[PDB]
Length: 215
Image 1 (cartoon, rainbow, N blue to C red):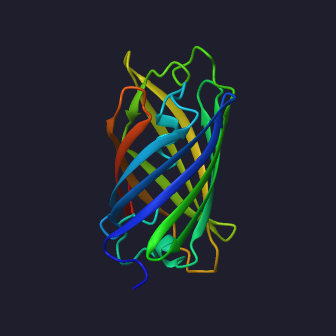
Image 2 (cartoon, rainbow, N blue to C red):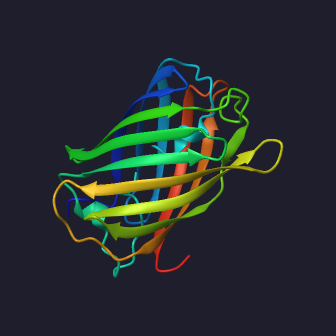
C-alpha cells in the first residue's frame, strides 16, 4: 500500500570523527519486501576523510528488511510518518560512535537525515589508519522493549593484516506513531562496499537483510 515493491531514498549525513567534520549526500534504491538495496554516497564537505569509511557504512535503512508473514514489520508499518533510530557503537579499542537518524516519506520516496559523532579513536588504530576492509555478515538481535524495537549486534570489521576489529552496536528504533511491535527475532545482514574511488569520496554499497525466527 504505502510501501511499494520498489522504492528510492535520499540521505544526508552531518558528522564529526576525532574532530574532523564532514557531510555526505547520497541516493539509494531497492525492493523493501525482498530485503535488498543499494546506495550511492558522496562526501560533499570535509573530504577526503582521514578515517575508515566502514564506520559510516552501516549508518546509510531498515525499511528494506524481508520479513515472514508472522513477524510484524514494525518499521514498514510506521510509514508514511516514519520512524527514528539512535545508535551507539562501542569499539574494542575504546573508540565510540553515536548516531541519530530520522526516516520519513515524501512524494513516494524515503528521506533519511543522519547525525554522527565519533571520538576517542586511537590515532594509530585501524579506524584512523584506514586498515579495515568491510564487515562480515552479522545477525542483529531484535526485541521489543520500552515501547520501541531494539537491536544488538556484534559487528566484525575485517583487517587488511588479517583478523577482525570488533564493535558492539546497540540501536533503538521507535515509530513516530504507535504501531504493532513484533516479538523477538533475528535480522541476518550482509553488506558489501561494491565500489569506491581512491580517496573514498564516492562510495557505493549493497545490503541484504532478512528477519528470521532463529540465527
